[PDB]
Image 1: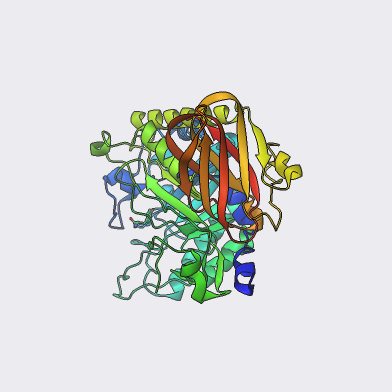
Image 2 (image 1 turned 90 degrees about the vertical axis):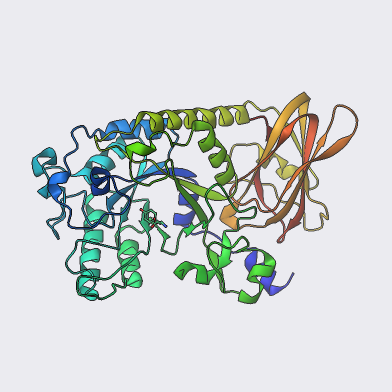
Length: 455
Ligand SMILES: N[C@@H](Cc1ccc(O)cc1)C(=O)O
């Protein structure tokens, strides 16, 4: 193997990136002034008197998120309109000036506390774009204000798992375009919350860039480093193939994808969209596609102006969670005999329920493969396979075969990348065994789990 391949096959996640990956799916909570004014885009300078939801019940939100199987929640602490959901000391444009809770409330506190009681991690979105704040457009003075608010959020509310950042901007009242001192912002986050992943407009987690309803066929976590300050764009179908990254040499990095979408057409709640909430089945397919396609899933659910998650959203979440649990429960009810093409001693690692142990074929194994034999003919429609990503991402082509009770065997399906998890789906079939052929790989693959199941 050449220097380049030895490099690519060993690019690896940091501690914070690995912990983040293991979350799999978490929620976004869009709630604030835009909810009250029924907008996707706020104008700024909205009257704080308009923020007076009568029945905020964050435990109702968290209850539904747990039932949905979420690992954490990212709250919109301040959106583009600039209204802050905590009583910031740096602006009067906050819940402290609203009639909500007699001006004595702190929704960031209320949410973070409830998240922790519910076993969910807590993250923040603090909008760089600010349509109210006076310093906006002045340059450094707005950076000072932003950093000031980051500091409040990152020091007063306990551990933060993610700081989510988009890059929208505009002109201030002075007519000048505000640009952000990203490097300065990153230092603050790294300093105050070392374990947090800085996401999207940050170096730790990449916006998947997919068209809604689509995920990459091949999602590589190892990609050109230039994608971190985002010729090539985040929306390209092929970011990480050998051909795509060839010319970049060592200028690549571990920069894993996050698929983000809303359960409704809009990010904020609009009553007119109450008949347009994704169903539990739509969410499940999404989960299977994202979390079964080497991407984390960020799912937005917006509370209504009353201060509750709406009934359809709660039901979809509940059904999503039920489908995910049924899937895992069947993935454990599975009785299989695992056999490998080499390193049979390590074959045990495929089924010990330890994500830290893996099977890796011998260097001279020219056809690495895992055979799973079933106690008797069973119907299956998917295989689950996971790489030991702590050590990198390597698999490039996977071919799955099934041995039918009727002597013969056929191809059940193929896939490219695996990474954190590949759930390969196909038509319901009855087999006595399946073989996973790792036809292509950057050096020897390290596989921590393999399984055949019926969804
Ligand atoms: N393209 C999206 C990105 C985004 C999504 C959610 C946000 O809260 C902020 C930004 C938008 O601006 O609408």
